[PDB]
Amino acid sequence: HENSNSATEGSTINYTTINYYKDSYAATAGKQSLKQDPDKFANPVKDIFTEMAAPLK
Amino acid sequence: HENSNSATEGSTINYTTINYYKDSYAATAGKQSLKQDPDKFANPVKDIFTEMAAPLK
Amino acid sequence: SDRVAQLTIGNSTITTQEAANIIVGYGEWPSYCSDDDATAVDKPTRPDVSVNRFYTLDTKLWEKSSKGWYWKFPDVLTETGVFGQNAQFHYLYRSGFCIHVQCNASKFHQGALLVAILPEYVIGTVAGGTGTEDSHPPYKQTQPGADGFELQHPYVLDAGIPISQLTVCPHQWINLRTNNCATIIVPYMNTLPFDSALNHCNFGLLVVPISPLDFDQGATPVIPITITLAPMCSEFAGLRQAVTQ
Amino acid sequence: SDRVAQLTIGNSTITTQEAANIIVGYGEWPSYCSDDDATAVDKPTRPDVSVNRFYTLDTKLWEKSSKGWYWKFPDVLTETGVFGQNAQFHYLYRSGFCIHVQCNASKFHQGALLVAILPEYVIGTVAGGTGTEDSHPPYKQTQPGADGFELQHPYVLDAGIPISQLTVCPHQWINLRTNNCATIIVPYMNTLPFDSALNHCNFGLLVVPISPLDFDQGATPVIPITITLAPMCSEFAGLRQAVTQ
Amino acid sequence: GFPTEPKPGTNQFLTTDDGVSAPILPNFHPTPCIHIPGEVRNLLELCQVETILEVNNVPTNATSLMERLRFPVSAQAGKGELCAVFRADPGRDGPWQSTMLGQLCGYYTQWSGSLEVTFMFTGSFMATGKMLIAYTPPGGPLPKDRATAMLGTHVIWDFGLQSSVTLVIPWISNTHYRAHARDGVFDYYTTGLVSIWYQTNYVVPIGAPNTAYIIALAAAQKNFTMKLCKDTSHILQTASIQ
Amino acid sequence: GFPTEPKPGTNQFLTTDDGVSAPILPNFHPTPCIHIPGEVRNLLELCQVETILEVNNVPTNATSLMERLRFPVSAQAGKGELCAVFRADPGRDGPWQSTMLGQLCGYYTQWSGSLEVTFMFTGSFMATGKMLIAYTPPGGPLPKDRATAMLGTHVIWDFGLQSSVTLVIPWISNTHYRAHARDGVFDYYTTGLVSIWYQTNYVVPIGAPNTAYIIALAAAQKNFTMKLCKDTSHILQTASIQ
Amino acid sequence: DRVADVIESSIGDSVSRALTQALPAPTGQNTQVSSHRLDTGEVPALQAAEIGASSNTSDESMIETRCVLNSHSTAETTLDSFFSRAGLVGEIDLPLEGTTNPNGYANWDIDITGYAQMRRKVELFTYMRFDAEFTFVACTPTGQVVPQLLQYMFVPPGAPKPESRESLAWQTATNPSVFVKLTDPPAQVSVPFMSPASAYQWFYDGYPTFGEHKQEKDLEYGACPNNMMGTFSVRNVGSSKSKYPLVVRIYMRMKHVRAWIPRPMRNQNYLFKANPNYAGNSIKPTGTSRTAITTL
Ligand SMILES: Cc1cc(CCCCCCCOc2ccc(C3=NCCO3)cc2)on1
């Protein structure tokens, strides 16, 4: 059927790859889901504020 | 259709293999069922006892 | 209700008051040969009680320096009893065993024997010491029958394999502070439904002192070890004249 | 309601009247180890209040020529407090941190410190100047504990990487005309659920003056910088005797 | 066997070819993946993070490398003096190379999107001042004065509690994408120039430093994207790794 | 023919590649498989079987090889003396090599799970005694005394009808798996140390041996697993098989 | 029955707070129409870098904007997209005459930090999990293809490392070997994420030994055993001298990538493998330099 053993196993992203062997890590890199989360690095702030506001109230 | 002539014929385990010839022994090793029976070698005792108990009553 | 036990087969009954449970080889009771597992087309003989019984074959003396002994099995029981006969007259033989090794001492003695069942126990030579000579173990060594044979290099079971691992085999220990006998029940084990009881030995019985016998002087020093085995579900086919070997 | 703040953990409370919000490392609050993420089968210790609190470990003096300092973390807090103890007695450790760096001056002073959290902050040597010698940073430099260590080549963070980019890491600035303290809250970050608090340092705390301290003469010239950190969701497992390193 | 006819390209090893291949370890099952903080999905997540722009990429004394990170601004004695100036091109040599964005660009042949450059003032609390940051689109020669610079996109920055101000460098281009701009001919892809002038002056009371610095930080706007990746040029080693 | 383009890896013979191959005997039908006792399905079935641990891996006289299987314990004259000590690492050189587990490990690069080590006392029935078996996790240096050893995972063993006691060496690790531990650097993967101290003393009446032995047997717990198999190192022949 | 502070005690929450969510970013953000805004109170352009967050000022609030439907893709900037490109990571010599690797066999410690291009890329992140496709391009030093048979064998840490061309380890009874003629297209193989950790670690700030940590041992600082994947051995398949000088180039291409904790890009030249040392005297700036901040 196919072993579920690739590096992106259980990942939150959905990949569609092609493979010819029992082991899924052999499969192609394939096309995948395009999600992002800039705020994790750009706005890791505890209390969000808006651009419209004055950052320091 | 395919000859039923591999070494694991009639076995109690279920294998899913790929093959391109009439003879099934040519087929890949394939993914298979994961069952085990430790007690056959670890607890081949006639009268089982539990861990909680004192082995010699 | 676990240290005392009684084994009754045929017209023989073994009693024990310090046994430590019973081991059933590979967790499987001896069975007769299935109709789809067999090939020999002749209807076999199943003597039952005349051969399925307790033969008390040998006694060894355990000494503060004993190395250990072994007995090849199918064979050990030939020439002795009706079993022996059916094994000589018939080509094909099949059977499981109930092995009961016993050895007692006092509460003031101490020691521990390893009692194992090693299937297809092939013996090897020291190869002339250096290892250049391709020697081979003699008939007297590979098929000693009763009386068994004494090990010369127990550490390697005279076959180049660690005894330290011999426990992956149906085994039981005879620790004197705990018990006074071992009881293994091996089923028929071969890659064939039947085979010649004569030239093929399904397994060997090992009895090795891992923790040396010892006792302060003055306590009876003669500590015997007695082997008692009993065939189970014995079947024989391929009847011809009687053969010794 | 954004420049003033109060942090309370254990029996410690930090007050600030000029802070500039709180950064939460990689946008994730410190959590305990999941049952499916863990491997250590022993039930861990979660001292809670006895170790999850504000340890005010060190003070540096900022001078018109200071280069910058760093503190490796898991370590910095060892030997000090009950946290220290649990970190020495246990093999495995796990925990997030609330780092609060503070430094004040007058409205007539000026300067700006960069305060970052660099995970797996490996230190490197100048390689004997020329680059032919394969030198290695000493225990005294890679694991300085409290007291931290002073940078010798901040431009490259003594590890061949531009400080100009150090901001892709949970950071906060201490611009004197704006605030007087930074507050980062880092979660446990490693490729393992637990690791030895002793020989592995999950991340380093960097405090570098990017815009030099300066003030007309006559204004108090002693401008300290104090580090205050607090473990969060501390967990320990693998108890043995106490170990220093 | 089943009739086949191999086409050109056979046996070739194409670096970027994404196909399959016989796996070395049958039935191998990797270590479960724990949950780890700060996972990245797309490099664009990084291009939006502000990093220090070395506007003052002049010093090289190795003892003064740290002063590239910020440029100065001090009490002027006149009207509309020029503070600093720089190419608004990201994948080009210059200040943008000290940034994280700059570096990631070196890995992609082309890009598109608006850029943002926040300027944080680090002077004393007592210092006042109004600067005029001006982005002059392509074709516009480096302005000779403020009155000229202001004709393009700009923003008058006032010093106050809000230390920094951001100058957005909108994506104003003839083309949909821009390959890296680099002097000869490829200056076709230039983004333009940024200049900082004194809207008024840096004012200070008796007792405060007569000179302070500004730190520039830059990144890409939400509409920023890059395509066709190559290898960086910015760097390449010399000695072989020991 | 049908257009095809062969990719890199073509014609390569990969040992562990599991594919198909032209069968030599058409229509061949193997000998029916009889029912045979003790069939194995997974090596893990074997790793749970206890085998003798050579804690006393000291003698080498070839006439004393048999005494490696058990270590001694005899009437002490003091308080808390040290009986024996050993690395709790399975795939490492030492006592664990005499075990079946030890040997199977040599075939797999990494492992995980708790280990169990049952100690059977073979002294006389009249001998009493309480031993303290202690497993000291990683980072913990070999304990200098009982009072120190006991600070880690341990168990006070009392001699009685139940000859043996088992010490479970719980899987206490920072990593999910452990590659084989081996002195240099790889001591990172060490499991810890096991030490046996005298909780009280070996007591005996007039008439019983003043010294007896303990036999150690070890295996893996139910949660034990191994991954990524390689070849054993423990052994490799010298002369070529005649 | 309980003590309250125990009923509350949020000690034991396995789930991470978050604060941020992942949204779909197939294309670049579009630009919506903007108009003049002359009002007090709302100041987008004003920010506070001290906070530690990147300015969130939109183009729209900085200038009057038109409407633009941005359909530019972001697919090429994903991790698989970025990292899944074969690159050189290892090189091996098997010369006839020399002192490097005669005897006809070589043991290459599997360490991808020996080649600057590839190294810098990955050192962008602290942790990285992924499968890979290794390709082996072999030939003579002149790039000439020769009828020679090699044997590549992956030797996991613990397996017996070959001591000679005719070593017994080449029986490769459990190790995975590959036999290839230099005339056959380069051998290529798929490799899983094999590590006891959950991700490879480019930087390990700490030691592995756990001992004293003297001067003579500072050699181990930064050495993380969860990356020591073992060695790659190669040998001409025979009993006698190879007859031709060989070279094997090892190319690795990652796939099914997961990366975490981005860090600053390598600024200086590289000097050694698994060791961020830099030339102390030759510390060059990150970029180019001008003559003054007021001129181009
Ligand atoms: C057939 C066959 C296939 C092979 C090679 C298999 C190689 C698998 C390699 C996986 C490498 O993962 C790495 C992770 C980290 C590092 C590293 N080097 C410095 C510290 O990090 C190197 C490799 O050999 N023979």
Image (tube, coloured by chain):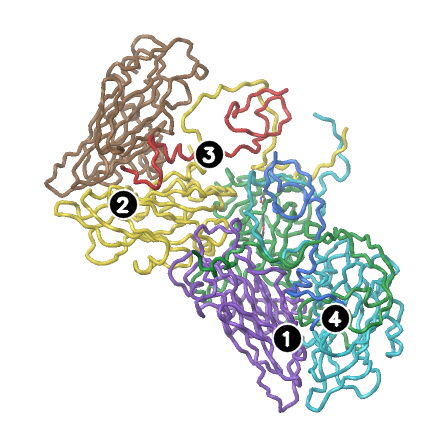
Chain colours: A blue, B red, C brown, D purple, E cyan, F yellow, G green
Q: Read off the residue under disc 2.
A: F214
Q: For the residues carrying marks 3 and 2, which lies nearer the camera in this image?
A: 3
Asked if disc 1 and disc 3 are in contact, CB closer than 8 Å, the reply is no
- Give the structural element (helix, strand or loop) at label 2: strand
C-alpha span from label 1 to label 2: 66 Å
Residue type of the residue flagged with mark 3: Gln
**Closer to the camera, D220 or F239?**
D220
Instruction: Measure how far apart labels 1 and 3 are at the Cα level.
Output: 62 Å
- Of discs 1 and 3, which sits in the foreground? 1
Report the chain holding disc 2: F
What residue is pinned by disc 4?
Answer: E118
Residue at the spot of label 3:
B36
- Residue D106, compared with residue C147, is above or below; it is below
The residue carrying mark 1 has its beta carbon less than 8 Å from ligand 1: no
**In x, y percent, where is residue E73?**
75, 81
Q: Which residue type carries mark 2?
A: Ile
User: Mark 4 falls within which chain?
Assistant: E
Q: Position of residue F220 (x, y in %)?
A: 41, 43
- Left or right of D174? Residue C227 is left
Q: Which residue is mark 1?
A: D174
Q: Nearer the viewer, residue C202 or G248?
A: C202
Task: Report the side of G141 relative to C107 (left or right).
Answer: right
Give the camera-side residue of C29 and E21: C29
- Say if labels 1 and 3 share a chain: no
| Alpha carbons under labels 3 and 2: distance apart | 32 Å
